Length: 263
Ligand SMILES: [Zn+2]
Ligand SMILES: [Zn+2]
Image (cartoon, rainbow, N blue to C red; front, top):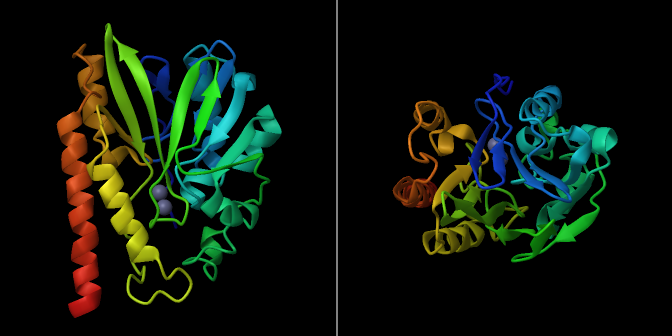
C-alpha cells in the first residue's frame, strides 16, 4: 500500500507561493487578490491536512478557485473530487491526462488493471494544453507538458518576486520511470520513450531557480525547511540542485532504457 504521508508545517516558499503539502506528497497554494490556486489534491486522507495547512497560514479553504495537479496518479489526484465538493474549485487538467481523471484510473496506460491505483472519478472543468497559462488575480502559471511518467504529466512554472529579486519557480511533475513500466514496444503507450526524451530536452533547457516537485524528496524539502526555520536566505532558491536533479533523472531514464534494451 502507498505509505501514508505525515503532516508537514505549511510555509511561504517565495512571493505568493506557499507549501501546504505533507512530508512526501507535495501540494502548493498560490494566493491572489481574486482567490487561490491549489496544486495537488493528494490522497483522500490528505484533504483535511491540506485544508488545515491553508487555514494555519491564515487563508480560507473556501477561497480555493482553481485546482491543478502535477499528473494523473492517485497520489497527486485522488483527493480532487473531495476538494471540488468542499470548495467548488474549477479543476483544470492537461488534455493527455483527462481520460485518466474521468475514469478514476481505469484508462491508465500502465495501471488500468491494478485496482489498488483507482480513485474517485471527477469532471474536468478546463482542458489544458502544452504552454497554456492559468491566470488568477494577476498571477500567471504556465502548464508545460513533460510527458512519459503519465501521458499528460505537467511541469508548472511561475515567476516569483522574493527580497526584491525575480525567480522562476518550477514544480517538476515527475520524469521518473515507475518499476514495471515498459519503454520498448509499449502496447498501450507506444510513444512513452519518445515522450520521456522530449521531457528531458524541455527540462534540461528550462530556467529553474526555485526548485520544487510533486514529491518532497525530489527537492530536499525537509532539510531546506530546517534551513528556512533557522532564517537562512531562501534555501528553496536552488538552481544547482534543480539542474543536478534533472540531470540525474534524465540519466536514470537512459539507465532503465539500456536495461530494457540490452539487459
Ligand atoms: Zn506518478
Ligand atoms: Zn507520485
